[PDB]
Image (cartoon, rainbow, N blue to C red):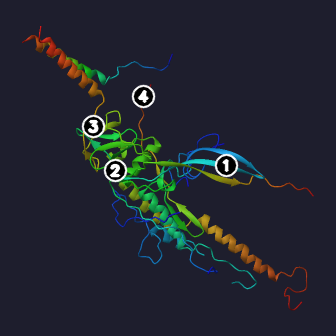
Amino acid sequence: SQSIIAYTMSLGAENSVAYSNNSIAIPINFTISVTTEILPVSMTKTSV
Amino acid sequence: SECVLGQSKRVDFCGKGYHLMSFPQSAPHGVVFLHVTYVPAQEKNFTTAPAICHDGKAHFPREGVFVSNGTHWFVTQRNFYEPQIITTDNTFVSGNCDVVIGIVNNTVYDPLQPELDSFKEELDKYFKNHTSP
Amino acid sequence: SECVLGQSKRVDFCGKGYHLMSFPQSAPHGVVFLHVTYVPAQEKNFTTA
Amino acid sequence: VVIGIVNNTVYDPLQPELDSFKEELDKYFKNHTSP
Amino acid sequence: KQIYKTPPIKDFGGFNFSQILPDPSKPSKRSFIEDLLFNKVTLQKFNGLNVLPPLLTDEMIAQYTSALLAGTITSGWTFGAGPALQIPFPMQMAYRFNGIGVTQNVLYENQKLIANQFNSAIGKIQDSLSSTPSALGKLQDVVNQNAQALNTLVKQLSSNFGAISSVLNDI
């Protein structure tokens, strides 16, 4: 039943952090990831 | 000049996360990078203390943060959990522990002692032998 | 990205003097930062080698 | 070769640890002569 | 990408952030410093001209600013480079001093003085913005120039442009 709908935008998933004056969070494992990045560097020439 | 020819500490400049290195690739009227980044995985909460004093004198880590699971105190890196026994070479000393707010109690090992302790037992054994003649 | 999400080591980029941290604040068609810095107080001469 | 250098004594923190151990060792040897 | 939120407890080792932290009393979730900036700046038409509203509402962007400030007050810099990890604020400044070559033992032995130093400096910001009227010249000139160009376009309609009359009707 797909149709066109209008709603309020979602800014993201709400998340709370437990803060304390004698608590830290040290990771035990890690990971390696790669990301792309695209940038224009030139434009086509034209002479009239 | 920065992402490829070296490692850049500018956060969120070469990939989202901690940068390692990058690889360029060509494109029609453009260029494409491959930012190889390092990201920590799932974590683990702990109990910490900003400082520690053994015989009144406060000790602070030379590099790292004090950590404890509730029974013993250790020092680990800030980005990879790796417990290590507290020793003299791991911490420098400055002043006493009557000023700092939030200090805890524990004893600090000294790595010079065990060889002396091994020698002290060796030395004490040598006196016992010399009593025979 | 630099001043807020980390402690930038660039000279005179996130406030006059040595940098510690920052605070973003909204504004109409703009943004305002609070660059917390660290500057030395009165000094004393000495002899070195 | 270095210019502007000045002479002075430097504390060796290992020395009192071994010296007091040796100083007490010296008294140990004198202690061992009595019996 | 994730909207963090600070705990209601305010035991930040003596540091005071009530000026920059959002105030729930106001109908809009904006703090003590932020409301003055909305007041200092002094901010559909006839001939086709129209102005469109921004996609992000002025209240919506106030949620990002609180989220950014909430993450950096308990996690530091780790929340921007992966999974957020919390840390006491009395120890976060110890790491920041390691970034300028001064040992961490300075902060712990002088925590009371530095806490007052930072707290006093925050208060001097609010009246500085309010008292001096030349602080927001950069933002105030953006609106004025945009309105100046838009206004002079309308006044150009009365130009004769070499004809006998300017009105399209009587000509």
Q: Which residue is mark 1?
A: B33
Residue at the outermost right position:
A48
Q: Which residue is mark 4?
A: C47
Label drawn at residue B102: none
Three-letter amino acid code at disc 1?
A: Phe
Label 1 element class: strand
Q: Quadrant of residue E12?
A: bottom left
Asked whether disc 3 touches disc 2, contact meaning CB atoms under 8 Å apart, the reply is no
- Residue B30 visible, this angle: yes
* Disc nearest the viewer among 4 and 1: 1
Three-letter amino acid code at disc 3?
A: Val
Q: Which residue is mark 3?
A: B108
Task: Pick the residue in front: B19 or E70.
Answer: B19
Q: CA distance from mark 3 to mark 4?
A: 37 Å
E164 relative to B114, above or below: below
E36 relative to B41, above or below: below
**Mark 2 belongs to chain:** E
